[PDB]
Length: 163
Length: 163
DNA sequence: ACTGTTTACTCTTTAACGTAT
DNA sequence: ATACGTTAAAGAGTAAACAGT
Image (cartoon, rainbow over all chains, first blue to last red; front, top):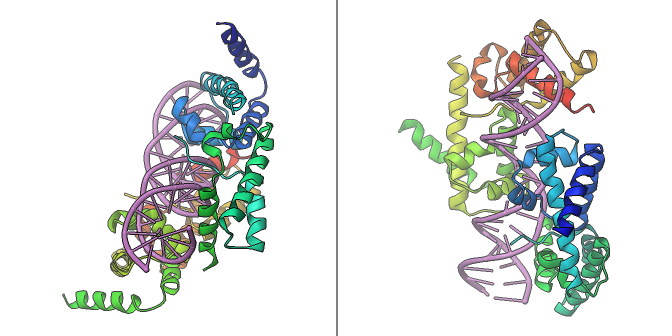
């Protein structure tokens, strides 16, 4: 019950501030850690179009409903650090990871395994600093950990858009 | 059977030309009549992804798969012209319509009922010309008919995205 | 292990709805 | 007849699988 009283207290104060300011906060946290909105909808129980509109535009939503978003934020933000202190969702390419990939697509559109392995760490390190963690805590990215196969399927799908 | 043999002839002639050339034809016909891609993948059985990627990008699909679309295209093309001569889908705003609606939204954000009725004709007219039929045959648009209610829900949902 | 075919999934966009006025 | 609050539906995007060289 100790951390509990803390968590329920944060839900209180977050329920007092402007929805938009506390919404832009939670969305940035989602993007930063590349957390799917489906994970929220699945656990919380709110409609997606409501979430998306609230997180992207500012559509007001009932305080009851909002609370559940804040309870999940506080609980998940606790979980991520625990997942990272120890070194079912689809992998999502991070924006920093995609920068290095498109850059390497200009040098070689068909790189070797070792050429992809070097790309793996440069992306997993760029993700680890987007989260705000040391790159040594890499397996904490979980379902979003970059694998050479994922780098492969990224390069293979990119050759499709050519023609 | 007399038109049937004709329909099978069009399906084969199109099955010989370039996928992309005849794909761009279908989308333009879908965009011209604001026909849901869903209608295709309901009546065909195709995959929306595969479909969407074929009409929007150059992604190929097998001749058997293609053929099903061409039979839908050829039969639906005859069915609409019939609908307009003898004159459950969601309504979709046309681009010629939306041009008028956004234009008057600058003149008045809350138009009178009669002011909306004037807009109704200017749009059904624009949609009919887009589809290439005389506006006297405006009952043929079916689920794409512009009603004053639809104009209202538009203007209402538009002022929503103002804050 | 690479190409091409097809796909399960995710997110946004949107017209309408439903409930209070 | 109308604001908000909320929602069912559509379609694009995407990572991945599956077959089959």
